[PDB]
Image (spheres, rainbow, N blue to C red):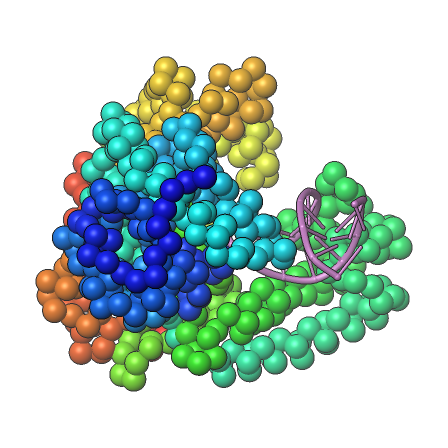
Length: 579
DNA sequence: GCTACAGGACTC
DNA sequence: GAGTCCTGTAGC
């Protein structure tokens, strides 16, 4: 039904200087993945090219990489990485539907061109699912469908650039798309593509230290329970824990009896089997998610891992790491921290470098909230948990017990999460009444934070959305809901979001600045991962000395606040040593 | 047999 | 508060 030329060769009018492009990749994981077809739509018409003919053509490939040749796209990073794997540069991408959709309403859950399209009531396109099918009946149809399917995506992108930008403007979010997300989209593609090398040996050996330890703990657990059973079944376990051995049921979940770690620790005194099992959850998590996790996704050719960072998914501005998730590798506990030693540099005589912000959320809070005693603390560069423990309890610095500090930590963390008086009482472990005297002690210690927490919920009511520093919206319909629980979750979001979100903003700018700076300074150093509040680079050892001074600087001047930002650095042989 | 949810646990 | 990914299980 939709008009187009199914082309046999590339012509001089498919190489206009404004054009919607589709480099369709179909597999969810785009690294080293087939490109199934190309669609171009411009001032002249609508064209489909087979990849093998278009990607062999030196004016097309020259057009792909020419930055004065503007392209609109949907999920251009998807596209760029595919083309990167084929040794082809893509540039001059000046509009990205996905990102613009994602900035106008992260809640919309946009994952294809069609959903991007509804937002403007454009229904002249099909959902990818409906052309390709779900999960494991997923195939690429014969060429007639396929070809029509893409020309409709390009045509839409062509047709919708204008309303989105039109709108983005109205929300002051244009600079945030052009100056932030899209440039960042380039950086990330570079990163994903770069890879992160793994010591597969180090990994198969841990891999096998764990299988010894597990089979030991696996027998013992049996020995103790008088029974073999599926220790990984949250069902058979609760038969063994609370049925055969009669243990107190402290907590329940809809299906049955709760077997979470937070519960197994209170049960610990009643029987040996508890702590041995606990140990097992721990080992199991390392073995199954991690040793096996990683050992499955390494390209056994280059021995690297190439995560995809999703840039259009979290509600707050945060990136997200998939296959493998490299934003959740173990750290708090030594047995698991040793995983970080399998991340190595990709070159002989290079090192891993790490830099993180220290208390980015709270500095951001001090800044938005404008609380003097929060700001002042940071201008003093204080130990903020001790400062709060000090303040919520009313005791001098040397007065502070370590149980008093881990409690003010919880209050701090709680406050950013806009936590409930009951909800902190569970977390901590005290009565709900005085758990609220804590909060009330906190808030008279920090008036200005109380005010922001008040005015933000109001400002979310009046307007329907909340806002970060860089103008990133989150819409909050469930703020007026008559359900108390649901209204309350919306409220927490009103408070926590401009914070988690303003941090996400700042770091993403630090990335643009650092990528520019590492270049401006002609350095071989490149970014490897971002993990919410830190950046990870790898560079030749010759370079560490300029980095220790360069990375922290850029990360710290990425924005101007009412308080200053602190970045700590760290470099070593491996991820693990960068500590 | 393939698929969707539920419970747990890992990071910031 | 914001994420991902694992095993088993409940059910087509």
